[PDB]
Amino acid sequence: FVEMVDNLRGKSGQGYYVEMTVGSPPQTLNILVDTGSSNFAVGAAPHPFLHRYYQRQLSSTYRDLRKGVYVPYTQGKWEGELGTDLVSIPHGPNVTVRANIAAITESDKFFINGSNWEGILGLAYAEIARPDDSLEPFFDSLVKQTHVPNLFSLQLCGAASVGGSMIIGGIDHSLYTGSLWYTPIRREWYYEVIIVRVEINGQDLKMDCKEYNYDKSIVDSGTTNLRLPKKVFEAAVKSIKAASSTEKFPDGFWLGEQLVCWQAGTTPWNIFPVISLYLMGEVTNQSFRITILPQQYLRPVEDVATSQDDCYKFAISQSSTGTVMGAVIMEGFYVVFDRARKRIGFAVSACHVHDEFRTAAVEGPFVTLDMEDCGYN
Ligand SMILES: Nc1nccc2ccccc12
């Protein structure tokens, strides 16, 4: 699996991408790694933001499915033409598979100007595929057509350019320290999980745990932030704001409507608390917790023409679609998407940014009663 180590790159805020090839002869494209969706879709026309795009006319192995897809998100969108073709991952397993590919022919607020990726690899399940669950996701095709075991793991690092590893078919123990702890995939649509308890600084939010998961909690490599549901984010920041009363900041800041700047080499690490999510464990009444530091929820914004300090975006925010464990969480951990056993493993990442003080942790077991009641139906 050392072949796969360091096969991810990116820039802060613009996600993590892997090199893939499509068609015969092979066309090289950089493809965003997304556990939050389930379509394999690639730029297929000369949109000016794109370094390159899929040229179906050049591929002897292309096949038209003669059907379109339309994919609207919150304020962005793409649209494309469905087909199949031969797909490899140069720094991945030594196999080639025939996968569905959406040739993106129109889009809005999807591709990023200045970015170095040209498509998206949806690694979640068929249930949330588009147009419907009959379009076989890529990882499904990979597992059917080859002997690649039904799992992948992600070590997301990064600082500027970011980096990481996507180990397809397995686990690389150099990527983590201590033990893996597993939480069940509650249902195979998103990578859905259940948070059973939340502590800020060790003190807990004493919230009905059902709220922590209103209406979903998912693990998503295509989202930067830890996103928390209205009511939970509400209480969430209430406690973080109180934990950090030493210094003052605007409301808009906590709303991600403003940035906050401290002078260089002089940010208050310690005036923010370590935050801990308890996840449902593998055994009745047993949980574990994963703990992140503010270096995860306080993310720099590279630079500005209108300033030159250490200016950070508060990486926690609200949602009407649920908790989203994005890069803020995943960069603290080696994350194992154990599809064969319907579970997600968390271990302390060998590349997480730590001090000589506080440190990301994955600890258990804890005793948590009524953890099913925490799931929203
Ligand atoms: N994961 C993911 N994939 C595509 C679009 C998104 C928009 C907002 C959050 C996550 C997304």
Image: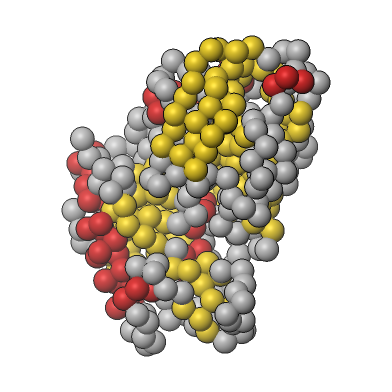
277 left or right, relative to 107: left
Q: Quadrant of residue 355?
A: bottom right
Above or below 327: residue 135: above
Where's the N terminus, which quadrant? top right
Above or below 86: residue 300: below
Residue 188 percent coordinates (x, y)? 39, 28
5 left or right, relative to 132: right
Where's the C terminus, which quadrant? top left
Q: Report the residue at 25% width, 40% height from top.
A: 375
Q: Report the residue at 72% width, 38% height from top.
A: 52
Tell me if residue 86 can be seen. yes
Q: Quadrant of residue 21?
A: top right
- Depth check: 188 or 37 in front? 37
Above or below 178: residue 121: above
Above or below 373: residue 102: above
Q: Report the residue at 18% width, 53% height from top.
A: 208
Residue 347 percent coordinates (x, y)? 54, 49
Residue 308 percent coordinates (x, y)? 62, 81
Tell me if residue 338 can be seen. no
Q: Report the residue at 55% width, 22% height from top.
A: 81
| Farthest residue, direction right | 25
- Depth check: 246 or 138 in front? 138
Q: Quadrant of residue 247?
A: bottom left
Residue 241 percent coordinates (x, y)? 32, 76
- Depth check: 238 or 152 in front? 238
Give the total of numbered labels. Answer: 0
